[PDB]
Amino acid sequence: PTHSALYAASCIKRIAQTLKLSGPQELFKLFAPQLLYTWLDNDSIQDIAYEIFGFSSLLDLLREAQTEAAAIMMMRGQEQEVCQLAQSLGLTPEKLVQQSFTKIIAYSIAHDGESRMRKILGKEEYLANIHLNFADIISTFFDIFDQEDPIEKAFFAYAAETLEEIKKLGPMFRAKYLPREIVHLCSRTQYEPENIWTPALVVFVARKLLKTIHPALGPLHACSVLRKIRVLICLAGDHAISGYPLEMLLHSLRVFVVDPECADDALGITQYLIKRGDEYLKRTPSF
Image (cartoon, rainbow, N blue to C red; front, side):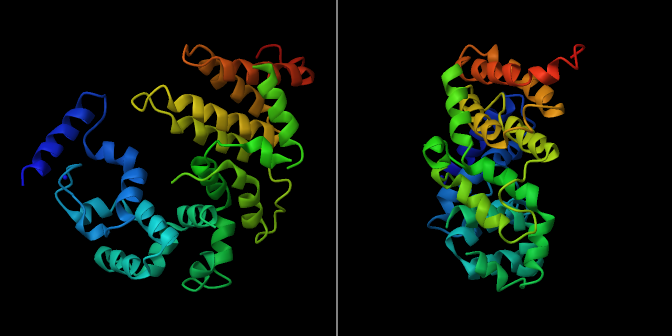
């Protein structure tokens, strides 16, 4: 997508209706990234089909698609179109960019344009926004990174052996980026890019990864999310094998071990965690 508008509308209503989903808009909430990317590649947001994903408006479709659309525009570059989005909304481009700063930086760092963010906010405000949105940015970095060849890039001189052990037991951007990406963001805050893996951040990112999976989204999603979790566990190192992170990971990886699709990934991570956290599991026999 004239009748094709109405037919696609009824089809999406039936898809999200017979899948334990709320409505058609809650089916756009799951797929807006890919649709918006592939469509805004060569088109403009203002002429999109607000009749699929029943919205009854374009200013209704926008009060949800600010973040993805704005971040993708600023990923490729449509400055006048970001300004047009902002005009249509009611908010000037500046407070808009202040609303969706996290995804903007996630994509931009992935697609390398941050200087273009400095030229609209400033050079003492942009850094305050990076300080305010650090963990959300790392979470959005683990969302979009594609699992291609992480061990090759690792040698970050400890992730390689760790991922090798966990493999011996049992918008998309390439894995080769992932370390350097983090570095480039963390060379503008105070916290050094080397060692930023306190347990709060670890549990944050891991819960994000798990929440990403979904029952309606397929049993092929899960094994990719699991590979990325293995990357997080090998990278975090010694904070994800002791304390509450250990308990929290053992739980969900158990749930992935009873999945008949792939119990090759989760059995390995589980062996590694149980074996390495022996000094801790002897203090908590009730768990």
